[PDB]
Amino acid sequence: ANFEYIIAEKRGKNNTVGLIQLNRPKALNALCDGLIDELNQALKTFEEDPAVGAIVLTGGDKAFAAGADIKEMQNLSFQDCYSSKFLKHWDHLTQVKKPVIAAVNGYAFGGGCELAMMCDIIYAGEKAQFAQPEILIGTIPGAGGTQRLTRAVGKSLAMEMVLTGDRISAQDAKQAGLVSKICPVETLVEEAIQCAEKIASNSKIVVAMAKESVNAAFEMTLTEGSKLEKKLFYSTFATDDRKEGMTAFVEKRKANFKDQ
Amino acid sequence: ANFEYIIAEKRGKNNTVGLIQLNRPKALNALCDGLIDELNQALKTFEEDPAVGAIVLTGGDKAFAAGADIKEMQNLSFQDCYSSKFLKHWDHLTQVKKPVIAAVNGYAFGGGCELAMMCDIIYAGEKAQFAQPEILIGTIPGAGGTQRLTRAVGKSLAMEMVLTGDRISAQDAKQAGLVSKICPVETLVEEAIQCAEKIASNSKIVVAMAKESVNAAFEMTLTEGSKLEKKLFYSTFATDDRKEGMTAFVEKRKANFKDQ
Amino acid sequence: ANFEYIIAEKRGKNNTVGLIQLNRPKALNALCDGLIDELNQALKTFEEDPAVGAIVLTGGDKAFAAGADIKEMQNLSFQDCYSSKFLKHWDHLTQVKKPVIAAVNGYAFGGGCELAMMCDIIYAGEKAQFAQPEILIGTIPGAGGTQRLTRAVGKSLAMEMVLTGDRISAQDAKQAGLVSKICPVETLVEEAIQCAEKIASNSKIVVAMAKESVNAAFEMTLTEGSKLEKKLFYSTFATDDRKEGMTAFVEKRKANFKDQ
Amino acid sequence: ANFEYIIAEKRGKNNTVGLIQLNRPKALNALCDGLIDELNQALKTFEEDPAVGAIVLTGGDKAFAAGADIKEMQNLSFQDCYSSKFLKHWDHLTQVKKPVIAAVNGYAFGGGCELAMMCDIIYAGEKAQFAQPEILIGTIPGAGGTQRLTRAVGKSLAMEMVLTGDRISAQDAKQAGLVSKICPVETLVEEAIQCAEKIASNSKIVVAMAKESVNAAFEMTLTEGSKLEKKLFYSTFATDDRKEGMTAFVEKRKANFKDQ
Amino acid sequence: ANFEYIIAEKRGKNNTVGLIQLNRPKALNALCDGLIDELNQALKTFEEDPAVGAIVLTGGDKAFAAGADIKEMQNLSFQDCYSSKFLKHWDHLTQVKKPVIAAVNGYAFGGGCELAMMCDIIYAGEKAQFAQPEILIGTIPGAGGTQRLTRAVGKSLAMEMVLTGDRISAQDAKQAGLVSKICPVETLVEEAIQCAEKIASNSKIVVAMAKESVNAAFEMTLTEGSKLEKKLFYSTFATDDRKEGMTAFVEKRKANFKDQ
Amino acid sequence: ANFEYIIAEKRGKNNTVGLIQLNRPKALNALCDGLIDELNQALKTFEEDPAVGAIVLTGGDKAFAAGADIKEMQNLSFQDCYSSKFLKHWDHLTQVKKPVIAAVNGYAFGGGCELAMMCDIIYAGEKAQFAQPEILIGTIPGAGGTQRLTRAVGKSLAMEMVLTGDRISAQDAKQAGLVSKICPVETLVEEAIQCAEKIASNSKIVVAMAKESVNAAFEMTLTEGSKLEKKLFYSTFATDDRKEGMTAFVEKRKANFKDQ
Ligand SMILES: C/C=C/C(=O)SCCNC(=O)CCNC(=O)[C@H](O)C(C)(C)COP(=O)(O)OP(=O)(O)OC[C@H]1O[C@@H](n2cnc3c(N)ncnc32)[C@H](O)[C@@H]1OP(=O)(O)O
Ligand SMILES: C/C=C/C(=O)SCCNC(=O)CCNC(=O)[C@H](O)C(C)(C)COP(=O)(O)OP(=O)(O)OC[C@H]1O[C@@H](n2cnc3c(N)ncnc32)[C@H](O)[C@@H]1OP(=O)(O)O
Ligand SMILES: C/C=C/C(=O)SCCNC(=O)CCNC(=O)[C@H](O)C(C)(C)COP(=O)(O)OP(=O)(O)OC[C@H]1O[C@@H](n2cnc3c(N)ncnc32)[C@H](O)[C@@H]1OP(=O)(O)O
Ligand SMILES: C/C=C/C(=O)SCCNC(=O)CCNC(=O)[C@H](O)C(C)(C)COP(=O)(O)OP(=O)(O)OC[C@H]1O[C@@H](n2cnc3c(N)ncnc32)[C@H](O)[C@@H]1OP(=O)(O)O
Ligand SMILES: C/C=C/C(=O)SCCNC(=O)CCNC(=O)[C@H](O)C(C)(C)COP(=O)(O)OP(=O)(O)OC[C@H]1O[C@@H](n2cnc3c(N)ncnc32)[C@H](O)[C@@H]1OP(=O)(O)O
Ligand SMILES: C/C=C/C(=O)SCCNC(=O)CCNC(=O)[C@H](O)C(C)(C)COP(=O)(O)OP(=O)(O)OC[C@H]1O[C@@H](n2cnc3c(N)ncnc32)[C@H](O)[C@@H]1OP(=O)(O)O
Ligand SMILES: [Mg+2]
Ligand SMILES: [Mg+2]
């Protein structure tokens, strides 16, 4: 379309996967205001399309995202940030009911690591790096860089990456638990599209319920989490795809889900 | 005894280890109602026996448990699931004060992985695979498959395993935090019995207090957890086994605990 | 000062690192009342000094800390725990706003792993062993050996280490998420001092805000944690170090923070 | 039936209300093991009856319950109270999905106030008294006397009632929030039965979902509580009673629910 | 814009109060989709206006709001609600940073009480009635009717109002804690406008901070609530209104706040 | 002792009550640093005395406490508020294991209401007024004026008191849940001393455990709180005061507690 910083397109088989690529080779894909607004518009378009079942958010081959534009947040004060709700349009990815895959190739510093951790699945290349360099410019992460990273890779590693700003490899992120699969830099997007197609081959309402159940593991207790999980498991016996799946399991055949 | 789906026997030295083996190779150890009732009866028997200190739950050599029997809940609706307390007898592993060790050899999909995660120690074999294939039949896990899995392996890996139904190897569950030790297939049961003997060689009340203190790490905050742990530690100076152990450590000898 | 159980000195470049060494080779650095009081005094002195930006806590080359002194708690009862509260001065390390690095060489059993887990960054040697052998003396951990360890390495591994008393290696602790970097025994102190220098090379108020934001990940929920992180990010635009760092990032130059 | 401590009968219009009366005029309805077992059996019978929609738990005209029986717990030690779970049969009232009305007439001290607070609706008479006299015998409440009372009447009033053992009137309990309606002594049971009839006149599944939604306000946060409430509101559009009620609201007629 | 269901106008002296009046006497102010969209637009306009400091939400003299439009959600199924995010535009009131005052005169049943409880201050009239009639139509409250009500009036009164549908008076809501002041029907609007003027007579950033500090008392713990409150109290010494007010208090004069 | 801002003395029968009076008629008992240090020293002295069972904090007949001293915090900035941990000594009252009774006569504005709410039992006079007038000077409460007040009197009343600064009466605080008893101005001290005597007439360790169990109702969930209460009840069987009280109840005599 008329997007300036992102490239929106429908990739994959049968046009069931949405690919949002960050195209900004002049600032290492800086998360400016216009880029975030275009990303939110693309996410809304992909969430208002019954043909799309999964979204893949990727960047470039040398850098996924360099964070927020430091050259846009420099001449700001406390009143100009608190009475303008700075970085309020960055919590729109966590309100998406469709799965979002984060293909990370290259530098993922500052806002890039947060944007990747706000996704369901994090796929990184063989030459990917994750770090929190906010401490080097006199600030701290403010979009989920000290909450999800601490519960994902551990307290010690998160403390180190936040207080030192050191870069970790994809192997360290796989060992700790930040990423789920290491892929080559030239085939990461293809494997991400294949994973999004696997995901989009299932019932959309059941996928949304499963995503909510998994996300409810960081907001409540174990007992209440299991109770909400059992309630959502009870509330799925009233759909049409559950019975179809159980019938295709009993009788040896393929399951055709009707998204209902 | 008269068990139709399980094999209950007292194993280990001095008959201090309870072994519950699921024996039904005709459905890959389907978690039906009768099997769950027999498992609960065996757990109650092993909890009302002052000679058993630890329980070892195991399955077969090709499949630990293939989940709930889908050939029974196929003709169930929302009314037959909500006001019938479906799967209500599956929360008996979290109410047992004695440690339960899970020996996974083969396929542990859905209900098997849930029952494994509801145990304290998870021991898997080299030829073992863990997955949650609920998204392929039109439902979601409802017995702890989206809460205990996310807090162990990570958000990304849990999201992938839930939304794709893919199978992970024992090495992946070991490097992620789901399995604590990788063992051969032909020696997993013996090493699990040895671990249960090393557990049942200490004070039963102190072991139960330690189990409660460890399980309280997912039900509240860090400060409240530390305070409850300190209170449970203060509540140990009123028993005889703590004093016996301290005297044996000071005098450099062996401690004979009397479970009191 | 005139400390008999610890050695306090200002190490590092420009005397910006506080090295607290535990010198008790006769009891494997037993955590007695006097040693803990001296540790708290050293921590308060290093906290009330404007020239210290990070603290490095270490022990010996064969044992970091063998836990609490059993010779001072063997003849205690239940009434001697609520009244004249025991282990009440061990919660002075989690109240320090400056980063505390832990260098573990040798045995870290009981109270040693508990004091190491209360630190932000944990550095272990190639021949370091972490364990919670409280179940072998009739007691349970009482200073965070069942809350932070469970959330760090996982439920299964923590259950095993607590109910069996077995020792793990530095490689397993790094793979599970207990330590952040494995260093040689003869060069662990130098790398810890270098990490403390790299940490103290930034603004102290921003480092304290980052430490609090990371520590608030085990005391609140994800939604409330994100809002608290956004608040702490908004509350840094009123300082001079943030603007100095942003200017040094835009006008590419060395950043000189005034710790204000 | 054959109950020697309680009187179980089916009261109300069309035999839709269960009335459990504590009959022990010699011990002021002491909460012994036999009485609690009979109460649990009566609750199970009323929960396995499709004709009963609400339960009314009442006592006598001078005392509802005097608390735990002292003549059976005096010769008990720590190893006889922490083991075997003495207070494990008293939490069978919060696991009931049918509404339980607690008609409190007379003395409600110790375990009686807890048994009343473990119900949905608390009805008190004119000469009603609530107190926590456990502090006068050297113990503390252990069945919800310091958790629900603190969140119901306030911190200060609960602190006073726990640390002093003073008795409060029914008017003070109504002004604070302990009870919701003050009824005469001679007509308390009749008004409780009428309230139970008005409750049972609605769909049982909808009433159970509403009870779960209300009870989820003391175990979760407001943000996640609202999400669980919306999910349970979504999960009611698949039943017949919701459509029947909406049709009887649109067209001027009465709603006849089929409990499905 | 020109509204047909609500009346948006600037009231009070100096045009500092925004009054939203629900004008639908033909359906007792039914909370339909268009009415909620107009209410959200009016709230956004009043929140993006640098002259409005508080909002007063009111209805009519006989009914504030009769709840959600039942004549539009009757022909809805489980799929048409969970995959359409029904009632997703009703959480736009708890995201407003400016204080919202609710003036209830008449019937506030179902969605009316839910909309009133999402406001900071709740002002009711003499002939005002609050109830939850959702149980009489086959559904449950789904917009905060079982979470914000239970934590205000008590568990027993909330259970009664939810499972019986009974109507309470303004005196009961004042004695329980649902409303803050009882005012006449012909002067409730004027006193609400005066309260909004007294609220908007202070600094807007400090008012927003206090509102967030009070709202954080239901989403967090007391210990972390105190820490967040102390942080928000520290983060106010960098504004121009705090020092102005302190200087005016020291010099015994009036403080002229500039919202900065 | 030689206190210039407070008056410390032992009152009550047998010198079992510690009366701490705030004597500063020139500033309406301003909470300055010296006054807070003296209050903390007096609290520590009264908590380390085996002849003191309860503490009674009070002020004057015209004003209990006017809050923090504005004359020493006017020229403070964000750097002098985040650093040095300003107001860190105001959290020494919530760490006392002995009950603290608050006698409020006159004005209790700002810090006075916070110090009163940090106590267990709140006793106000007939001429007492509670308010949070921080919004009138440009700041917000920072010592529990927005966390305990919201849970005590409700959301609406707390919002009004914080955003308007209006003063409430003792009757409103009692009907809302802030205070527990209304007493005359000249006899409030005698009734508080009698309440402290009735509290100190029991076992100190059991009273401390009850206070902790009541305070754990604002930091944990309902299930976890009930479980911690049950654990404390089981631990109470390790002292002699419980057995003495039960024996005195069985043999119908007065119980003599020895705090062990
Ligand atoms: C809640 C959110 C919090 C935050 O995210 S705060 C910001 C956090 N991010 C950072 O602190 C670091 C951002 N980037 C860098 O430090 C470095 O770059 C790299 C480490 C990524 C390495 O890149 P290198 O090889 O050194 O080249 P280069 O010249 O510095 O970058 C090329 C162009 O990219 C612009 N750029 C890089 N990062 C940002 C950014 N965060 N905001 C705005 N622009 C950025 C640069 O300035 C420059 O542009 P020009 O040629 O015009 O000078
Ligand atoms: C809260 C609870 C949630 C849940 O657990 S929902 C259910 C989730 N679990 C699953 O979806 C796994 C279902 N099982 C399978 O997908 C496959 O099977 C396996 C991958 C485990 C193995 O496949 P293969 O090696 O090809 O063997 P095979 O012939 O399909 O199974 C052999 C026999 O075992 C029956 N069986 C397997 N799983 C179940 C099951 N979950 N419920 C009932 N029966 C099952 C089969 O049907 C068949 O039996 P027959 O010969 O009579 O056709
Ligand atoms: C809140 C939680 C509190 C707790 O931590 S409870 C206690 C938990 N900690 C433990 O259980 C560890 C106890 N220590 C040991 O088990 C062993 O030691 C080692 C595993 C560390 C192996 O050390 P080895 O090579 O076998 O030599 P050695 O002779 O036992 O130790 C040398 C000296 O060190 C003293 N010592 C060791 N640990 C402690 C301790 N925890 N408290 C007091 N002293 C200790 C010993 O007794 C002995 O001293 P001497 O030669 O005078 O007899
Ligand atoms: C997890 C929960 C733990 C708990 O709840 S512990 C319970 C807390 N402690 C109490 O409730 C005891 C306090 N009760 C009393 O002091 C008095 O009772 C009353 C306040 C109820 C007033 O009744 P009055 O008639 O004045 O005294 P009376 O003569 O002792 O009562 C008549 C009969 O009732 C028996 N009884 C009273 N309370 C209990 C009880 N809590 N447990 C067992 N029996 C009780 C008595 O013993 C006696 O019977 P007999 O004289 O023939 O022996
Ligand atoms: C998350 C959301 C949850 C919910 O809110 S679900 C819905 C829950 N709310 C209710 O159930 C309230 C419904 N009960 C009533 O509406 C009763 O009535 C009253 C208690 C308010 C008594 O009012 P009365 O004096 O009997 O008059 P009248 O029957 O209401 O006629 C007035 C006109 O107002 C329409 N109306 C009233 N409430 C609603 C509504 N909630 N939705 C749609 N229309 C409503 C009526 O139908 C009728 O209209 P016409 O004259 O055209 O028949
Ligand atoms: C985390 C905590 C945050 C906070 O607590 S902020 C402080 C509480 N916030 C407030 O805004 C409270 C202040 N408002 C007042 O203090 C009013 O006064 C009163 C309503 C309490 C009393 O009014 P009146 O009867 O007219 O007496 P008066 O002449 O103003 O006070 C007599 C002397 O007392 C000094 N004083 C009163 N409050 C404070 C205070 N909070 N800090 C310091 N001094 C105070 C005054 O200034 C004056 O003294 P002089 O005669 O020497 O001028
Ligand atoms: Mg891990
Ligand atoms: Mg109240």
Image: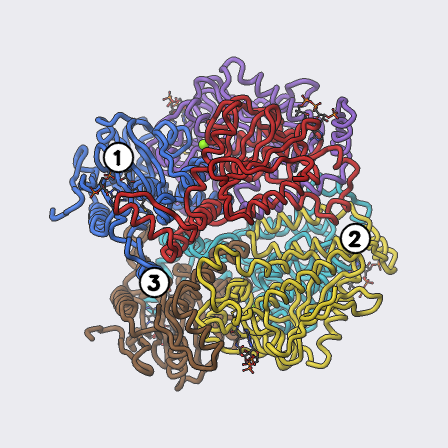
Chain colours: A red, B blue, C purple, D brown, E yellow, F cyan
SS at mark 2 in the image: helix
Residue D59 image point, x, y percent: 34, 76
Q: Nearer the viewer, residue F51 or C174?
A: C174
Q: Label 1: how many residues lie within 10 Å, few (<14), some (14-19) or many (20+)?
A: many
- Ligand 7, seen in the image, is in the quarter at top left
* Chain for disc number 3: B
* Chain for disc number 1: B
CB of residue at label 1: within 8 Å of ligand 3?
Answer: no
SS at mark 3 in the image: helix
Mark 1 and mark 2: span between their CA atoms? 64 Å
CB of residue at label 3: within 8 Å of ligand 2?
Answer: no
- Do circles 1 and 2 both sit on a common chain? no
Q: Is residue E42 left or right of residue E83?
A: right
Mark 1 and mark 3: span between their CA atoms? 42 Å
Can you tell which of label 1 and label 3 is closer to the viewer? Answer: 3
**Residue B10 sits above or below residue D92 on the image:** above
Sequence-wise, the earlier of marks 1 and 3 is 3
Place residue F154 in its image quadrant. Answer: bottom right
The residue sitting at the left extreme is B1
Residue corresponding to mark 3: B79
Mark number displayed over residue B253: none
Q: Looking at the rendering, in which quadrant would you find the N terminus of chain E?
A: bottom right
